[PDB]
Image: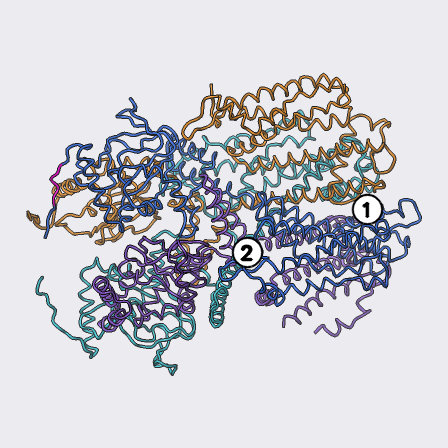
Chain colours: A purple, B cyan, C orange, D blue
Amino acid sequence: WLFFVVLAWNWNCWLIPVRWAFPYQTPDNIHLWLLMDYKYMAFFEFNNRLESILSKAYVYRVIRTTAYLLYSLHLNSCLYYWASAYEGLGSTHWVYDGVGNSYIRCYYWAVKTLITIGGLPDPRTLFEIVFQGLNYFTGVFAFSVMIGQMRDVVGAATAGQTYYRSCMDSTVKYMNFYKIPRSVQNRVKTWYEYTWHSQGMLDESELMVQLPDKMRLDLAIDVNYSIVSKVALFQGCDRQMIFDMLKRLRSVVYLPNDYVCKKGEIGREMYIIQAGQVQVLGGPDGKSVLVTLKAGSVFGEISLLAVGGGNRRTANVVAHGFTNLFILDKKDLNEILVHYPESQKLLRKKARRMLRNNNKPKEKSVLILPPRAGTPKLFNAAL
Amino acid sequence: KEVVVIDPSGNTYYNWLFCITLPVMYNWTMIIARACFDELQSDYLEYWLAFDYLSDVVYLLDMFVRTRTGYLEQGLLVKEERKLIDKYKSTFQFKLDVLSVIPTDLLYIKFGWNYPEIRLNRLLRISRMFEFFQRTETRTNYPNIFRISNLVMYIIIIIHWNACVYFSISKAIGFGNDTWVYPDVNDPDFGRLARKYVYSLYWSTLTLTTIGETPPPVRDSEYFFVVADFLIGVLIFATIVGNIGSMISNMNAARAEFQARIDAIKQYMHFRNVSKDMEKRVIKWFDYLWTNKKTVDEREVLKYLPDKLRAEIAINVHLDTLKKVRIFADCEAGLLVELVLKLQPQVYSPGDYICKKGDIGREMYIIKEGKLAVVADDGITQFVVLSDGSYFGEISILNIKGSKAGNRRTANIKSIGYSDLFCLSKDDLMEALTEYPDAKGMLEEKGKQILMKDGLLDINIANAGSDP
Amino acid sequence: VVIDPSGNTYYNWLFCITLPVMYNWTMIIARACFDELQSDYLEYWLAFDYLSDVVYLLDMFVRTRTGYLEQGLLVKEERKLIDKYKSTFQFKLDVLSVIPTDLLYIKFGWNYPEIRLNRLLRISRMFEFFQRTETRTNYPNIFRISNLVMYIIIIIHWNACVYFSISKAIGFGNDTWVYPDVNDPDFGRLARKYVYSLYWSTLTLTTIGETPPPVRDSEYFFVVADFLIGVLIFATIVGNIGSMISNMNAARAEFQARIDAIKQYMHFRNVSKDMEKRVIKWFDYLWTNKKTVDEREVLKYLPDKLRAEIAINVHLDTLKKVRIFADCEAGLLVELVLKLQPQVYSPGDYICKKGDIGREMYIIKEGKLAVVADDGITQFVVLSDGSYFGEISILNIKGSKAGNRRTANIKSIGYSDLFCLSKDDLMEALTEYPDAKGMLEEKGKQILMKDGLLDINIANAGSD
Amino acid sequence: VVIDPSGNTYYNWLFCITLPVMYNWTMIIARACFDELQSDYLEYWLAFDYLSDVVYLLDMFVRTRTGYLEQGLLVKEERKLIDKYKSTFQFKLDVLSVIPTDLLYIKFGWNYPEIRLNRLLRISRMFEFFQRTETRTNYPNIFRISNLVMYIIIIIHWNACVYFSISKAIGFGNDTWVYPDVNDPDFGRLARKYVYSLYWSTLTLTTIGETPPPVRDSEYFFVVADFLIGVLIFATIVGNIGSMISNMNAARAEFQARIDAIKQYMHFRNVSKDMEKRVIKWFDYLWTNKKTVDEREVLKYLPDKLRAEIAINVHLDTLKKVRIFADCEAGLLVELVLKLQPQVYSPGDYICKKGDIGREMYIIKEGKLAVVADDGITQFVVLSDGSYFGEISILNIKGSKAGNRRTANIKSIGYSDLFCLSKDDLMEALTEYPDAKGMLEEKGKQILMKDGLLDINIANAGSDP
């Protein structure tokens, strides 16, 4: 409906002017009016739709505005013509004898007298000053709204980049407050560059809070179901518990030659890999690279069970470069298990069985699960 | 000493303000437009010498209603003179009061009847004129026509002043001694106050729109004049465009924010490949959020009000249905108030399984407008409609002895359209009950009564109470 | 024999330096480019050069008398300051700007008295005088707009001088575009030429091209360059003005945005109209009386000590008079002081009711309250200021007559603004000093002993 | 060969490639329309055309180098780059611009360039160079306006050339509007022929018309374009400059807003004048230096791995010079230092007076402190950098027997900027190293046994059951 409606409205608003005052045009080609004489916001709504549905969000407003401008030009032309007709004389008494040039000289006269430039005309009678004033104002209005739209678009376009430099130069001046050696400058610079590129944002958490609830769960269940809901340690329990466990997770990114488990430290964390590759190293010497995990793997899981890494981590680890592995701490584990004490007893029983087999036996891979993973069965069954 | 006082915000104030505007606006034009010409002065002074005195006496009256307006002390607005006046006498804004009423209509004795330029004082009572429509904007229905109307007014008065000045300078060299200046006048068709003014106005407007369709200067006094005129026209243009730009930027700050958020969510979604069904669902939820204009959240909309107003609005909006629940009947409202103060909304999407199976269900859910149904494990016909005010989840919120394997309801419920219900919490009910140690017994007694009358397996074991 | 780099004596001397530099910046081009202004007013122009030279010389001594701070105190020994100035970048700029270059004056006679162009670079001092004077203005938007206009005038001046020079270089009257002639009776009076050239330059820099057409080669180049410069100038001006007008209308927009948000919501849930009017009048009151902002976030910028000093200076005179704080040590008092939370009421509000929780100890500041029985109006007592209204419900003691009931029925009369104090905060505060608690409860029990004291016998705690 | 897409050498080659890519954008039009200008110097036309084509094809020396990053591993490929580029886009133009072009003008001579049209396809190096350079400069202010100026000059050049072309098309002198005529000195010469046209071009591009009526149809197209593009040019330049000048200053505005709010508060509860003096002096000392920030939020969005480096860089020497913490595993200081907070501080204030039950750690740093007894008289030993006093209270040592006193009456003389640390923070931070707790406890015990006065020694367990 919109296409034909706007065509018809442009036609009926534009053809009539020259067909009421300009002398030799209303009977000359009287076919369009004769055969087409047969609170609006739908046009605005569908322009809104087209901006949304099509890549362009500016051509529609541009064409509407320039159509308004040329419509105003034509309407001013017609109204001064009718002012002359009502008064009898005036309004380009010499149109230069022909429609083919009458049209062009008419809108040339309109664009000439657009604001106040005058030129040829001289004071003839009353109301001329007021006439020139009104035309002046309408021209100024159209021009001003054009600049307004332009600055609108420029500002709305170049939005986050200014903030990006604001962060960067603020922190560089700060860090420079105390004369710190260059290495960390280079490190922080490349960190910032890599983060900013290919990501756009800087901390996706702040989007999560603004966005509602009850769909964040759907996002998390569409993203991180697999790797977690397969590990035998947390296997086979209340499905409605793991959801909070998931909801509290946090990302991090490392760089080349990055210690993560420097041997001889405590540790309280279970890492997990999303897109990268890390090497289980065997010391600063010739790289005892036993294996390098690829993706969808887990590491250091036992340390979350009542003792964080046994006051000394398993083995040294370093990274090639950019890793992007998630992180999950222990406080979350204890809080989720106290909210849902259904499985706290079974995880706890596994923990005592592990500590009781940590001293007297070795138990490489023979008695790990069946006595540990056996305790989930009856324990939560006692809920 | 008990004088009556007007309210400093009542409609009387507004109407008197509209009264005191006409005279100063009249004096801001007619004095100079009478100094310029001389064929209205000494020609129409009959009505003029009358119209002047009414405005003088209205100025005098203006000096009055200022001293009888109060100013609150401590929720109390002082309501007597002899100190309603001391502050006004001691402040500023009284020097103008001294100056701008002095009758100097005697200097005409040394200046005849051809100098109505002696009245260069009535133009100091302008703060009131400003304030009138500086303030009336906040009372109107919709602004954003008022600013442009004001700018139009100011520019028009400017051009009138300049059309005055041009004639004033013209009649100092001789009518017709040049070609730039106004022509000679003793000839006919020229000099009857209908041509002596419109022509000047035309010339002034052309000159200040600065395009140059008039004969050029020749005498070297106006080489100053035209320069100054151009240097003022530029500033006029700058002011109008800057003002309209700020206006047009301000009245659109919602769409930009909404589009920025949709941008962020689109980028994040297409950063880790998710099923496209989620894209469809997410976008067909965002459009729903936008369409009924529900972008804001009830959490933060209300966060700035003082606490009390929040209390009254909350109690008004919802206590009826809480008192409509099938258990809370004989509850001291000194509890229901803090209970109501603890509600949090939930809003849902089509085809969401709320509980659907054996789970904990440790909350309280009451339905607003929306449709819910209870089904079996599979996608079959509904068994009951939770049409308009239905609710379950009540008995779960407590923990009574000898329950029927509590907090593991296995019913199957599901949303279809859009629901937007509300939620409560067990722990909060505990903490807000802590201070009324009498109802708890009644509540648990009623719960045991209903559970027993439900024909269920309450183990009904006697309590221990062995050690008090 | 010293001064701070921030005292008003330094400010006045900063103004004092400013007078000659602006003077030097303008006259030089005109008085070397018209050649009529000199050759007849020389006696006017001995003392000015003398003055400017000696002013430069004396000022070059200031930089070795004003110290700087050494981490806690102002350096006040010159050798470092002499070393400091020697290390300053501007010192060599000073030396360049103070060079006596009139050794060529005799050699060049008076062909070019423009050789003193040297003394034209100590302008950063004018710049910092600008940047230091906006910080202490009553209302500075006007100031900056004035500075803008000053700059525009200066540029117009330079353009006019350039045009006249190019005309005299080409030769008077060989066309219909150059400056017309010199031997006529009027275009020789030294007053026509300056002003005509000013008019010329302004008409060129404006938008329309309507002046006499060009013929020669250089003038098309000149015209195009001036057109471009003019466009740039106009853009700068409009941008600056728009920036100011935006910064001025800041608050009102967001204020009305908040009000609109509230109304938009309050339409959604079908609320009643009376509170509509109440909230609207509330907003209007708070707007008019210039107390729109909320005090909490307002205060928390200063560090600890200053915040504490402000806090004590508006409260440590009422608490000194509460009944039960007869013999409390200062530290406990201050620790209490820092936990008072503003509330505000309006005429006709039930601040409390009968027989409910006793959980606060009000201390009114600037209001009026009265106790009205619900039955009609039977006002008993009106309280002016410094009213306790409490002071025992917090200090819980055994055998309370009616533990935490407070059947009083008070009500505000109009627009009172009262602080408050909680009880968990009192416990957390008193935990530090485990001594006074006993004496406080003791004297409170004595106060009760003067009247009723209980509703039952003493619950003697003879545990030990 | 292998290159990284972020390196100074890569920028230098970008500058070299972008240098001769504008010849193809300007000189071609002049030589196409202003005939007999090439005839002046054909010893330059081809003499630079060869250089242009040499570099224009040597650019592909890098489209096979400069590998793409993969899975967080460095660009280290030698054969997948070429077929990557081929499968992807930007290879089509990279050859479509590269017809040898010498097999058509042979039908027309070695004189004119208007068949070099297709070499106007490779415009990405200049765009990329412009966007890349600004992220390294110091003064991003002038760059954007310089860029816009260049663009405007170029479009003026185009319009001038097209006007003279359409002039050449029609008979010269048949109307005043067209270029006047030839067969006349300086009206049939070169320099005037284009300068005058340029002047005419700017005049007509400005909307206001000083021109005759139309000759016939198909001439008004010029003024049509003139207004249609003049409006857009002016609008965009104004918008850009306005946005940039607006954004330039906002810190001043925010500082002023804060000062305004605080002043409105203070002159409302009848604060006495002296306090107003003190607070305004403090905000002065704030703004007149570079101390006008709060560093806590500055380091907000760093990774959860850093700041221990710079931490131990700044807070380590004096902290290691203490008589309680010295015996410790470095992990202890690593956990500790990360939790401190600053305390800037104004001259002339008693930090602590005799009689005080405060509990905090206080480290002097780059200032001057000094303690008096009772009335600011008879100053005792001065406390220079790297010092403190007391600090034993922070731990509830058994038998402290005099704690909670701080009988010092300490005072500050000049701007001090010392440091602070809480107590419960220390207690929480000792949830992993229980062993050292006993040794530090006994250290305090022994030091207060002799250096401290007589200890009570009667401390014992209370109610066991």
Element at badge 1?
helix
Residue receiving disc 2: B252
Dot 2 amino acid type: Asn
Query: What segment is highlighted magenta in the picture?
Result: D456-460
Residue at the spot x=32%, y=56% of the render? A313
Dot 1 amino acid type: Val
Question: Which residue is more in the foreground, B44 or D261?
Answer: D261
Residue A274, by quadrant, is: bottom left
Q: Is residue C431 left or right of residue B47?
A: left
Q: Is residue B53 left or right of residue A24?
A: left
Q: Is residue B181 magenta?
A: no
Q: How many marks?
A: 2
Instruction: Judge whether A213 appears above or below D158 on screen.
Output: below
The location of residue C416, given as percent across then percent down, is 33, 44
Disc sitting over residue D195 in the figure: 1
Instruction: Judge whether B118 appears above or below A375 on screen.
Output: above
User: Label 1: how many residues lie within 10 Å, few (<14), some (14-19) or many (20+)?
Assistant: some
Q: Are marks 1 and 2 in contact (CB under 8 Å)?
A: no
| Residue A39 appearing in the image | no
